[PDB]
Image (cartoon, rainbow, N blue to C red; front, top):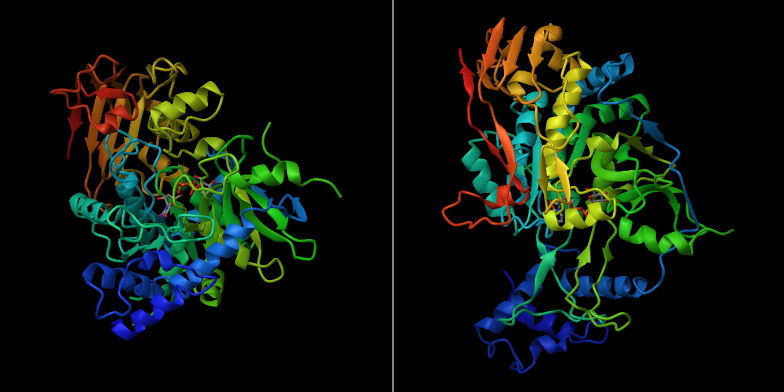
Length: 585
Ligand SMILES: O=c1ccn([C@@H]2O[C@H](COP(=O)(O)OP(=O)(O)O[C@H]3O[C@H](CO)[C@@H](O)[C@H](O)[C@H]3O)[C@@H](O)[C@H]2O)c(=O)[nH]1
């Protein structure tokens, strides 16, 4: 595509004052023909960048200057207060008329919802060498985050549910491999891969090179998802196809928060009840948390009010700098974003999916402009909220219980550090434990009589903290459908006759109704995979066996001839699946 002539032009352009990328061409021949393969190839990806980024490498460099300049000054907003449109979600564990009404309205709206999963990130912190969505939500069934989201979306939206996954060079091939291995058949799935952007070796925005002498690249953030969608087709633009098909909402989720399946229906219901074009999923924030804050903002004294997320790392500078004339003053945003499709599309087309950018260089010294590592420009998918003026649109937030936010983000080591400071662990152990506890709270909400200790059953991270797992109850999507309280009531139509001991394990797959059961041990019950089949009904069942246990992974573990995997080690315990009764048919 790129002619040898065009390449020389770009080379010369990049050497001009204000771009100053002469260091890339040190020791090069005057003209292209004279240049070799290595050289001609470097000039190429510089050139091709145009097709990946607005205004190519030249504009990228200019944006860097503008950002690096802005990044020296203290952030400040003329005004900062509570967003006008904030709404409290009813508890997920109380079956009130309101909760019922909202779940019913929301669950119906799921039939007309487009789903989007951002799964391009590496999650540096974890100490898991594979992709985040390949993590199990829990080790009872080992269902991956990927499968969990997809089966749920196909359940509430039908097999043909529109679904977008954003990958990156870091996650893409493994994502496709996982889809293939799980034998997930998702007809309207679109996998969209974000491209990498160049890096700056310094505050003057000189491009960094790697060891071999090639242009160093890094991801541009979860912000890329909007442009990826804008430019995606199916002949016809993707979003057009969705609109023409009758879809009315679009939802964005992140890679390791199982809570989203619970919050989303509620949000949809509230978005429609309160006519919200954009609806931020929130929780009460603890002053220290690495989650952003939902605020009403005016950056300068003359600007309009803008409802938008302010990231945690920024709310620090703004904190002390801006004021004069148990939780954070403003809601914490968990980045489950709920949009009215038509409103979303309008702003998308206006901006070409392009959202405001930033840069957050890491310095090697206190106050030397020297970079410890090359920096690149970033973007946040939630910053699309900046394109929604208060005049034309209604942006707001829905506040849920903190318990419904269950990310898996920190390693065991970090988690011990956080917990010693009294902060949330948000690690694999607490993620799995939170999942089990969520099923239990939901089930008790429909009257299932679960009695169980609140004491931890295992300690992790060198006696730092403990979690409990039991009793373990996991119902698959065929069994539990959307997971609404009404849907759970269908599995247990007479919950007072179902007695699950605190040490028990109940796994249910397919079309199953449990009327009466006494369980002291582990039990798997399987019904027809076909959701429209005659359900396997369980009455007067009595099951007793050794069941399962959990124990900690000990420091004195050889790791040799041990089937202990990273998945085990990052949570610090292992389930022992000693006995299991199985009821089929
Ligand atoms: O280049 C990227 C970077 C990230 N991601 C994904 O984006 C999501 C969010 O990434 P994560 O690294 O977990 O957290 P932060 O980006 O630090 O923060 C976000 O997530 C928080 C809650 O988990 C919110 O409170 C913040 O405001 C929101 O910016 C994940 O699913 C990642 O896979 C990509 O797809 N491409």
